[PDB]
Image (cartoon, grey):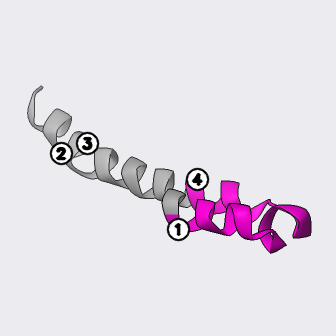
Amino acid sequence: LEQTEKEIQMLDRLYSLYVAVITTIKGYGDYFWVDVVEKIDEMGEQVQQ
């Protein structure tokens, strides 16, 4: 069988991309009052996001 291969990829690749998008948002979200309140890492948020 060959069709279900492409059928699987066409959805799975970009669903993986969009969960990876969630990954960075949550990774930054863990950052503290120390990490966020500081103006030296607020610039980090625009950089990373």
Callout 4: SS = helix
Under circle 1, the secondary element is: helix
For the stretch drawn in magenta, what is the main secondary structure? helix
Q: Earlier in the sequence, mark 1 or mark 4?
A: 4
Helix, strand or loop at label 3? It is: helix
Q: CA distance from mark 3 to mark 2?
A: 4 Å
C-alpha distance separating marks 4 and 3: 22 Å
Q: Is residue 28 left or right of residue 6?
A: right
- Looking at this view, name the residue that lies furthest to the front: 40
Q: Which residues are magenta?
A: 23-46
Label 2 sits on residue: 7
Question: Quadrant location of the N terminus?
Answer: top left
* Image x and y of residue 38, in percent: 80, 68
Circles 1 and 4, Cβ within 8 Å, touching? The answer is no
- Residue for badge 3: 8
**Could you say which disc has been placed on residue 23 in the image?**
4
Q: Which amino acid type is shown beneath numbered disc 1?
A: Gln
Q: Which mark is residue 46?
A: 1
Q: Is residue 35 magenta?
A: yes
Could you tell me how far apart the alpha carbons at marks 4 and 2 are, in whole angstroms? 25 Å
User: What residue do we see at 68% from left, 54% from top?
Assistant: 27
Mark 3 touches mark 2? (CB < 8 Å): yes
CA gap, disc 1 to disc 2?
A: 36 Å
Rounded to the nearest angstrom, the CA distance separating label 1 from label 4 is 15 Å
